[PDB]
Length: 50
Length: 49
Image (cartoon, rainbow over all chains, first blue to last red; front, side, top):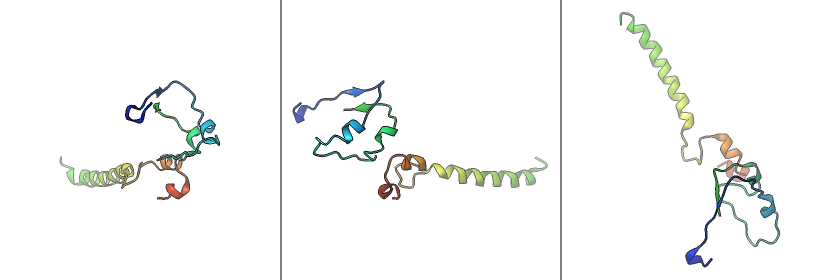
């Protein structure tokens, strides 16, 4: 989407593999706020919004 | 009520102690009052703050 009209999707009832994103060398940036990017695989969420 | 003086001593100590316990839930500026929520999410350079 265009930034003025950004998309949103809900993630639920699933296993969230965060190492697959964190250790992907293709990202130019990966900055987490309030949580360490390396502890994400050990955490549970109500849901996740992307 | 005849024994109110003794009951009063008991009530005051109980109240003081319950207050001490309730204070553990205060954040005092923290993201969470729970020490484990801090530890399970942040790396030491931030967790320590």
